[PDB]
Image 1: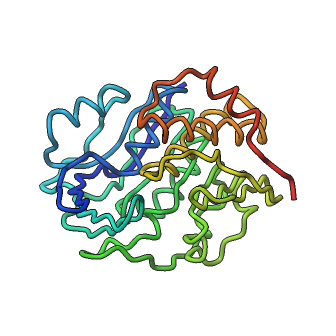
Image 2: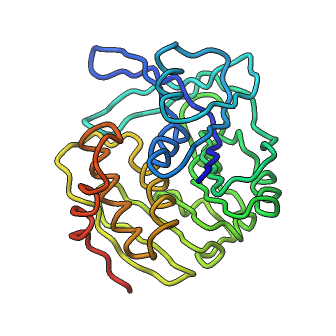
Length: 273
């Protein structure tokens, strides 16, 4: 299997209490990390320079295709408790307006902040056979400073195989209905989410992990669901995706056996409304 993941990776300048650290971030990183358990992943991204160690982390699990840029997307993250953090945009890499040629089994769009235009999802839906999307970076404003969400028309999403959003983000998709996509996944942190198969609603419960930190959870969930749905029917894929995400949150990595996922998945609650 060959997968293309599209979106900026990010230099996060992270403040927790009186300590500052930098770390690689961006939904594209986390989606690719999950999908790497299922396919040969390539990441189409943009940045000017990143720490050698981060380039290595990226290349450990994917091939990089980098749109030339004078800038690197950079956020200041300031934690307010064990898991909530404020994001402020400081710098932004080049837009990504041209996809590569060649056949990909999965194209997964996961931008940070408007670098992938909706027009590219539209053209890709005609050219590529299978497109998955995380909405966050289509809604989040690319304006400098504190993160804000602005509404967008969601008509361009019709034909997407898999769409992921946070429950709180869904309000920003206007002119959208769940049957526009084969599968809509609506996350709500550690709380019960919703999933739609051709417009028909299911509820599901994430695994009740102990750890508060949830960086990348929704991106890993989308990537894992994409991976499992290629092999498994809908409900099983959902259960396995939830379990995979749980083990990622526990381990801060994707080094766990598929056996451990399957065992955990059997207990995941899913109900057809």
